[PDB]
Image (cartoon, rainbow, N blue to C red):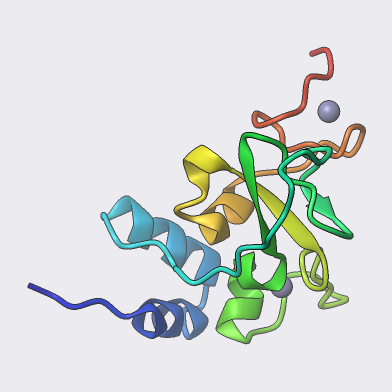
Length: 128
Ligand SMILES: [Zn+2]
Ligand SMILES: [Zn+2]
């Protein structure tokens, strides 16, 4: 059985003392990723950079509205920095197609190369 409910998951995380860990542990337990991230119409011929002013998905990505892929925005809670600043809100986020089932998890787990603007491990081809 069990019917599933996005709001159940978001409620659980929103009211957790550590929402990021709550979501991470929930996924690790086999939980269904947060759905309904807002997928954009785009050419799929963009730069493939992680977080952009307009959609920039390449052939191997999807572009989504940034806030819809942000755990803190989606939970309607303050962001984890003194300023309360969200890097995603008002922007567009590119998610590799293999991970597009869980954009919120993807943005939580991953980091952007400050040099090339691509996701580390998913686009950055800078020398190591
Ligand atoms: Zn946010
Ligand atoms: Zn890079």
